Length: 304
Image 1 (tube, helix red, strand yellow):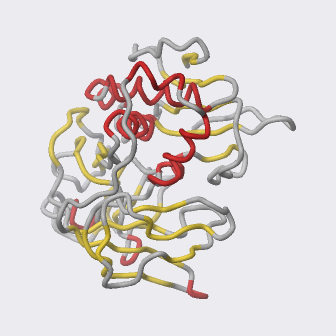
Image 2: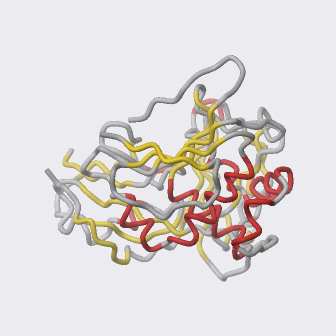
C-alpha cells in the first residue's frame, strides 16, 4: 500500500534545510550562529553542552533565517536558506591509506565535520562521547519495511565510498565492524576486522565492559566521501512513499531537506500528513519540524 519503486531519480528542488534539535537524545544546544549569519557547508551551527565537543554543522551554505523554539525554549530547528557553495574543507586521503589512519585523527575530522553525530550508542541511542571508543560498530545495511529504500540500490551507486567508509570504521573501532545485511551481495572491505552478518528493527548486544555504536549505510558512504574527497557529503537517497504519492519511488535530496518543498507537486490533492522517517517510527513533519530527520531515510505521506 503506497509501496515505492526501487529506482533512483532526482527529487524536487530544495531551497531550505534544517537541523532538528529534539531528535538528538539528551542534546542541549549552545548556539554558534544567529539569524542573519551566512554559513558555509560543514560550518558549526551549535554544540551540545551535555556532550562536550560534539558539533552540529550546516548541510548547506547560505543564511540562517529561523531558529525555532517551543515549550521552555527548546530548540526545534535551525533553518538555513540555500545560497552559494562555500564550504569548510578537511584533509583528504587515498583509499589505501584509510584503514591505517590514526584513531584520534579520524575522530577529530568526524567531529569537526559534524559527521560524528551519525553514530549512536546502543543502549541509550545518543551520540558517543568524543573521548570514548567502541569495540563493535554496527552498520545497518538492511530494512524490512517495504516502504523503505532498499540499501543495495543506493550502495551500488556508491561502491568505493561505502568500502572506504568501512575502512575508516575499521580503524576507528578498537575491535570489529559488523555489516548487518540481507543475503544480497555487497561491496566488501578487505580489512579482516570487518565482518558481514547475514539475516534470514535491530537488536544490539549489551555488555558491562563495552558499548555498541550504530550507523546507517548512507552515513558510512558519507564518512567514506569525507576522507576521500575532504568535503562533507550531504547527498541523500530517500524513499518517498505513501498512498497519496503519485509516483512512489527513490529520490535524491539533501540532509535536512524541507519536506514540504520535497513533496511539492508529488502528492494528490487533499490534506495530508507528511512524516519524516517510517510511518510507524517517524515524527510528524509539520511547521518547524517539516524537515528530514538526521537519521531518517524515508518520507511518508498519508491522508489525515
